[PDB]
Amino acid sequence: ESWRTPAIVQELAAAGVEEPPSRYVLGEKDRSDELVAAELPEPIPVVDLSRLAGADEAAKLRAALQNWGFFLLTNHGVETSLMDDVLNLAREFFNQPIERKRKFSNLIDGKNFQVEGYGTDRVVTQDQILDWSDRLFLRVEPKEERNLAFWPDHPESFRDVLNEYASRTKRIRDDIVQAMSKLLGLDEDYFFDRLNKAPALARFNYYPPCPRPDLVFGVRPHSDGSLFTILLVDEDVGGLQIQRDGKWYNVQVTPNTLLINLGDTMEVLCNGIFRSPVHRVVTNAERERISLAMFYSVNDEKDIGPAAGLLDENRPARYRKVSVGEFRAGIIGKFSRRERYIDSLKI
Amino acid sequence: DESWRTPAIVQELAAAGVEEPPSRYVLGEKDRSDELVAAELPEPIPVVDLSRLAGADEAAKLRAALQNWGFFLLTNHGVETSLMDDVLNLAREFFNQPIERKRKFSNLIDGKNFQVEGYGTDRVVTQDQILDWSDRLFLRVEPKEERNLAFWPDHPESFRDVLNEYASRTKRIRDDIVQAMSKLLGLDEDYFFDRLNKAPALARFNYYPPCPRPDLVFGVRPHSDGSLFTILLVDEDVGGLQIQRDGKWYNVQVTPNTLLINLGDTMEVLCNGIFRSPVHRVVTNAERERISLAMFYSVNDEKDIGPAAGLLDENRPARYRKVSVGEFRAGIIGKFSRRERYIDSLKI
Ligand SMILES: O=C(O)CCC(=O)C(=O)O
Ligand SMILES: O=C(O)CCC(=O)C(=O)O
Ligand SMILES: [Cl-]
Ligand SMILES: [Mn+2]
Ligand SMILES: [Mn+2]
């Protein structure tokens, strides 16, 4: 539409067009020698969850979070069948006649936008540049505010499998949070008063093949606004890239393994001892890419600011203190305008 | 100096022979008031015969122990006398080694980086944290995927075989106790067993050295266990374990070759406070050391920890909040460091 109903990017790829529409083509500064990325100069940071209680593993986590802000997780205890099934739901739901899929459109009545549903993100302005990907955004926790009406019916086990996956990742959320609290010198339960009744958001990404991968981004360069994200990818074959010291690095998520990356809230909360990585996804011209991201956010208990226990007067606050509503307003708000909120809070 | 993150081996401090504990072990005046001399049990220690726990007589003895005390002694427990002696010999022979042979298995990795598993004490979070007058060797025996054999000691040479054998006996005990208590609650005997597969089992060998000022320190601070159940074995108890009931402190001597079972905080939550997990502590003495082994049995991450649905109705509301297993565990461990009781933050 004009800008009220952006078209589903999967239908633009199935049109067999050789060029993308003008609303998807980036600028010259964003299309400079960046999309041709390198690969990590060292073995990709890998944390073994089943051994994270040991100080050896906790030091591997520390180096991952200090150097890169993300890592791959192994021996995480999520069954291979469950990871295959939850990704089969996205595979099955996305690979559907579109009349079936439009029933869960995040543009209710075709004109009013919301975050929860199937489609793309918010289009504030007509000249805004749109990503070459579709999404299915679902709030999974707390279960009391779960909007099942937008949860797809096909396959007929979507709610059960996604709920099962949500309860598996909970243990991963708890273990990693406990580990980092010890790494930061805080109480190992420090972060759990901020997680009671906290939002858990599931994002099903469909990056369709693009005839011109040089002109578009699967998702724009960005850092997550969560505490951290668990990422699950279906036979990655590439596309995800992460930035470190200006340079984009190609990161491939090995099948049956999970990628954990930090969000902007964690960087502020830990005063920037670990940082939230800025990342993006590149499209390819042959095959599509489906990923499931689980965002774990903080409740409205306390304001988002550096932890009291990480600040003496010789380690002052590098970041401001803002409310939860102000924080979330800007991660979403600055995502559309292609800026990074957390820079504005840095002192 | 930040050397306070590298806590001393208390057994070494005790061998210094000086007249006072260092100030970091000294309790506040409130903790040292008219408690440390406890009272004697007004009734005999509750005792349960495991071999007859399927019978009404013993199971009723089990209920009275759980409702009134939260703990009981277990007889005919299936653990041979030689095996209890063997597992306590591990503790005796390991601790009575030169500090250089024990330090290989320190939980302070590279001398700096704390982890739970190993020989030392519990996490030192702040400089002003009061420390306990004891060392412990903490070994993760289950699940085997999380087992780290490199911290299981090389002395005596039977350590892995003996502890494995003992733990398999105490696991059986755990199953029997869970079943029996399930029937007490009117639940199916297997109601909780979906929480017991690939669940943590932790062995804690405690070493309480003598202290020149037993009036000033705790061998271990007042606490309830975070487990479902705890099975405790003490080497010739001589004395020191104290348990609290309704604000009063009582001495409890774990008779040799018997096992003390106490209910843990996880069970208290799961049974909605029908039975409660008892607060207990160890006081030191000036003459001799005390050795005990505690097997903590926890739950997996199948469900969040909360009151069992079979125990709730309109006139039986839930008395505890529901929290995830990892959140529960980190709260147990964190609150222990701060001298606070985690389960009270879950009470509704
Ligand atoms: O699809 C990926 O690999 C990245 C997903 C991502 O960054 C997101 O959903 O926020
Ligand atoms: O040593 C005792 O008698 C008590 C041990 C104990 O409470 C523990 O290890 O948690
Ligand atoms: Cl239940
Ligand atoms: Mn992201
Ligand atoms: Mn205890």
Image: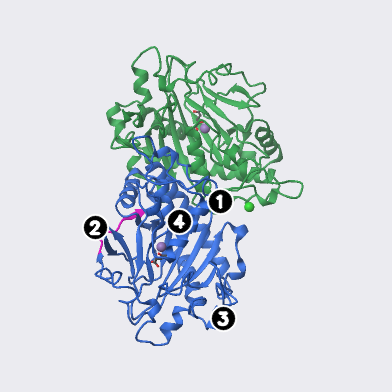
Chain colours: A blue, B green
From the viewer's perspective, is the residue at label 1 or at label 4 nearer?
A: 4
Q: Quadrant of residue A56?
A: top left
User: What amino acid type should be assigned to the residue bearing mark 4?
Assistant: Ser
Which chain hosts label 1?
A: B
In depth, the one of A262 and B43 nearer the eye is A262
User: What amino acid type should be assigned to the residue bearing mark 1?
Assistant: Arg
Q: CA distance from mark 1 to mark 4?
A: 31 Å
The residue that appears at 68% across and 49% down in the rendered structure is B187
Q: Is residue A91 magenta?
A: no
From the viewer's perspective, is the residue at label 3 or at label 4 nearer?
A: 4
* Circles 1 and 4 on the same subunit: no
Residue, disc 4 = A226
Residue, disc 2 = A42
Compare marks 4 and 2 and give the one earlier in the sequence. Answer: 2
> Dot 1: what SS?
helix
Which residues fall within the magenta stretch?
A: A39-47
Q: Residue furthest right?
A: B315
Residue, disc 1 = B195
Q: CA distance from mark 2 to mark 3?
A: 45 Å
Q: CA distance from mark 2 to mark 1?
A: 40 Å
Crowding at label 3, few (<14), some or many (≥20) Cα neighbours within 10 Å? Answer: some
> Dot 3: what SS?
helix
**Mark 1 CB in 8 Å range of ligand 3?**
no
Instruction: Classify B348 as above or below B81.
Output: below
* Circles 2 and 3 on the same subunit: yes
Compare marks 2 and 3 and give the one earlier in the sequence. Answer: 2
